[PDB]
Length: 149
Length: 149
Ligand code: HEM
Ligand code: HEM
Image (cartoon, rainbow over all chains, first blue to last red; front, side, top):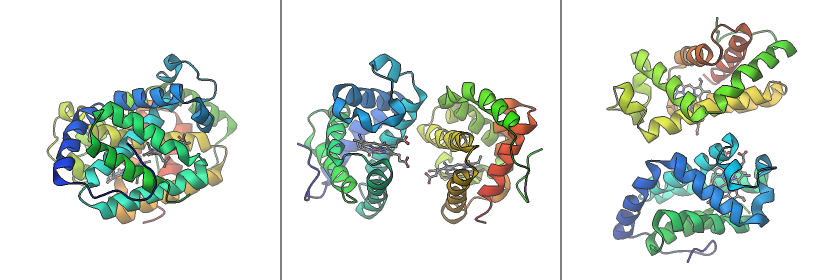
């Protein structure tokens, strides 16, 4: 499963290749992909809904998909992941980016760090439900997004 | 016209209101708006094309609108402006954001500062062709994006 603590073994050349493949199609239409994922996560995880101030008032999955605020937010998340995917070969760069992102969440957005793996789960279940290699990537991302807390 | 040097008078309550109105519709579909603007700017201003490394190979306005890299890039620009519009009342905040953005362009992206006003012109011509109040906002944005150079 997806972890957000400790450490995970390096990604193997085989795993990286599987990821790039499973990913490519999803990013080709991140506009949509992104929105669905975020809408799915949000509608099914009420406890974290209070952390998206700009979505106050939006309850149905219908309204959300029509809000430009939901789309922007969803588009940024989906690309942060895309950035990671693109840095799988430069673990150095991937860290700097996410560690910076971790800081923003902890100091400015003040979001509960427990949902990182919950949303990561939806992204994984959507992009490549079942792949363990992709679960590693999401675990690294989660572990790093919590580094600032 | 749009300036990127010196200073400009403060926005009047009247101008701000005109701006918010002319903007709202555009942002409601920034996904599209953004792409068109960026595609227009890029296709008609060759001299600045070499500054978008990720667009190498893309020449027709057809290819561009299909590239996820163009879309992401266009979506970020369009929102930076949206951020400004939202800060028209807090000139303080608007500065910090843009001054930071100025730095990234000068130190990391290494873009020629002369195109800020050229692209700003297309955004203005598209969102509210003719409005002088909107030209002020774009001027403030341009003056600030050059502060780091
Ligand atoms: C799946 C892992 C996640 C990634 C990679 C991620 C990525 C992002 C990105 C790319 C941004 C833009 C940062 C910026 O504005 O400069 C961001 C902003 C934000 N994130 Fe996360 N995020 C993740 C999970 C979460 C979770 C679980 C929450 C909390 C429920 C959350 C709440 C927010 C909020 C409140 C903002 C800013 C809202 C705004 O001003 O639009 N994020 N995130
Ligand atoms: C209309 C004024 C402009 C605004 C408000 C603006 C805003 C932005 C924003 C928000 C980003 C991303 C910042 C980040 O994530 O680090 C960006 C990136 C960038 N901008 Fe600008 N920009 C403007 C004009 C320009 C111009 C005219 C050039 C070209 C000469 C330029 C070239 C770049 C480059 C090279 C990037 C890298 C993005 C990438 O390909 O990944 N920008 N800009």
